[PDB]
Image (cartoon, rainbow over all chains, first blue to last red):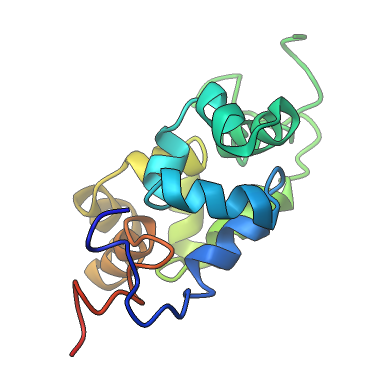
Length: 84
Length: 84
């Protein structure tokens, strides 16, 4: 919401914006609110689940997203050697 | 790397794996390398371009990816920061 994030021409680049909308836990409603509360990927992944719950307004979306952010490429690949 | 990372099913869950591969600056060679240096999205977005150049071995890929990680959804659109 700073001078750099406020788009004059207002195109909305379908790279990073769309990048959100394809993530589990994201809808356009909470994407736009997100978009105002986060910079991009870095800060999005830096945000806690609780922050996402505040932005998205649902712990469902927040958990889905937060979990997707933390799910290692080689995590779910295992079935549960260390049973949690 | 530990027993943690060792895939039982060796499925390689496509979701986050492919999530990398679609990012500008990511190729399978540097993705696999990344995959060994990065947990998931959070660590990727936490890593600096220095780290990316080390992992990917290319400054080109590192710069492309670093840019993508740190460019707000509307930042490319914002003519206040860049462009003419």
